[PDB]
Amino acid sequence: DTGLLSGSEERVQVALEELQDLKGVWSELSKVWEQIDQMKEQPWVSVQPRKLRQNLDALLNQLKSFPARLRQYASYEFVQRLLKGYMKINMLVIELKSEALKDRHWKQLMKRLHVNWVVSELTLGQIWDVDLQKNEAIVKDVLLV
Amino acid sequence: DTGLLSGSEERVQVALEELQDLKGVWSELSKVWEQIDQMKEQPWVSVQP
């Protein structure tokens, strides 16, 4: 018998508590991920942006659901900035259902984004995966003309 | 004594069974016209014929 390493015990305790916290975080983040991916998967050129915006608010509610223990995490801030991401989706939103969305417009923005699309399925998850927050200049120029 | 027409209550219970069957029928029909409503609501984005 000797002085047992209470440092090891407290390490185990903090690992366990942070583990449960991160598991709740993963549950919330998985729900966010599935909902946003299911949304943006569709081209969304036939759906008012407000049908998107309410999801935004729902996402906000989810971002407000958990206590402050997650709200101090880098994942929380990342999701909040991806909440600004959903806000600039609300931006684009206007281009997707705009009358200016034309075949020549399609091809010109296609060259700008350098991506390749199949017009039959407007999988909006891909169009967001081409980050508007990253390619803002080219998409804004394409919006202008 | 009050000999009562129990056939009234027999009709009551028959109507009850008919009502339960119709409740099941209309639950299924609620699902059906919800799916129809889901369609009727689709402003139509990429849905295929």
Image (spheres, coloured by chain):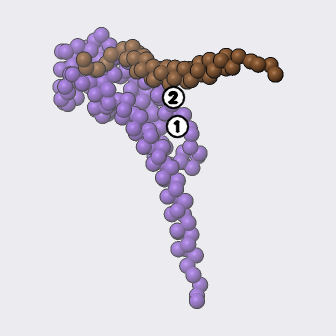
Residue A139 visible here? no
The residue nearer to you, when weighing A106 against A59, is A59
Q: Which mark is residue A62?
A: 1
Instruction: Name the amino acid, label 2.
Output: Asp
In the rendered image of the structure, the colour used to display chain B is brown
Secondary element at image label 2: helix
> What percent of the width, then of the height, locates residue A28?
48, 43
**Quarter occupied by residue A101:** top left
Residue to which mark 2 is pinned: A57
In the image, taking residue A48 as reference, residue B1 lies left or right, namely right
| Figure chain in purple | A
Quick one: quadrant of the C terminus of chain A? top left
* Pointer 1 or 2: first along the chain: 2
Chain letter of the residue carrying label 2: A
**Looking at the image, which residue is at 38% across and 29% down?**
A39
The residue nearer to you, when weighing A117 against B2, is B2
Q: Residue furthest bottom?
A: A1
Chain letter of the residue carrying label 1: A
Quick one: quadrant of the N terminus of chain A? bottom right
> What percent of the width, then of the height, locates residue B13?
62, 22
**Looking at the image, which residue is at 56% across and 66% down?**
A13
